[PDB]
Image (cartoon, rainbow, N blue to C red):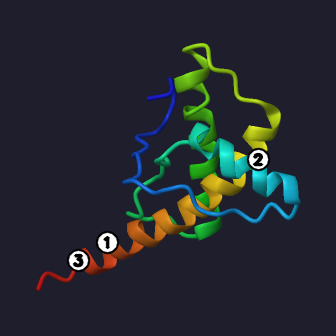
Amino acid sequence: VVGGLGGYMLGSAMSRPMIHFGNDWEDRYYRENMYRYPNQVYYRPVDQYSNQNTFVHDCVNITIKQHTVTTTTKGENFTETDVKMMERVVEQMCVTQYQKESQAYYDGRRSS
């Protein structure tokens, strides 16, 4: 727990997507430095929620407050640029993550 976190669950596993920062150099810089960013995202269970917006952005909030602290406490030091790029990343991650947390719920709750 990040010294707060009301129960937050970690993700599953996703990869490096191919972001669209809309600057040529940004698309290069990320293509090299993408490994700095997390391979999972922290979410809340779908068990009540409403609004994909807040699922993704509270996920992005916490995750960019977790994989900072988790690493920024070991003497890594995330650049400003990395932090803003990581936003696009963890946003597109947690989009796909909520597709699991909704579907694995709504389909898991079938049985046979």
Can you identify the residue that label 1 sits on? 104
Q: Residue at x 50, y 27 (%)?
A: 2
Q: Marks 3/1: CA distance?
A: 8 Å
Which element is circle 2 on?
A: helix
Residue at the left extreme, as displayed: 112
Q: Residue at x 86, y 59 (%)?
A: 24
State the residue at coordinates (55%, 55%).
16
Q: Position of residue 47 (x, y in %)?
A: 38, 63
Mark found first going from the N terminus, 3 or 2: 2
Q: Which residue is mark 3?
A: 109
Nearer the observer: mark 2 or 1; the answer is 2
Nearer the camera: disc 3 or disc 1: 1
Q: Badge 3 local density, few (<14 within 10 Å), some, or many (20+)?
A: few
Relative vertical location of residue 56 with respect to residue 65 in this rendering, above or below:
below
Residue type (three-letter) at the residue carrying disc 3: Arg
Determine which quarter of the picture holds residue 68. Answer: top right
Q: Are marks 3 and 2 in contact (CB under 8 Å)?
A: no
Of residues 23 and 2, the one nearer the viewer is 23
Q: Amino acid at mark 2?
A: Tyr
Q: Secondary structure at mark 3?
A: loop
Which residue is the site of mark 2?
29
Q: Tell me the kind of residue under disc 1.
A: Ala
Mark 1: which secondary structure?
A: helix
Foreground pick, 87 / 7: 87
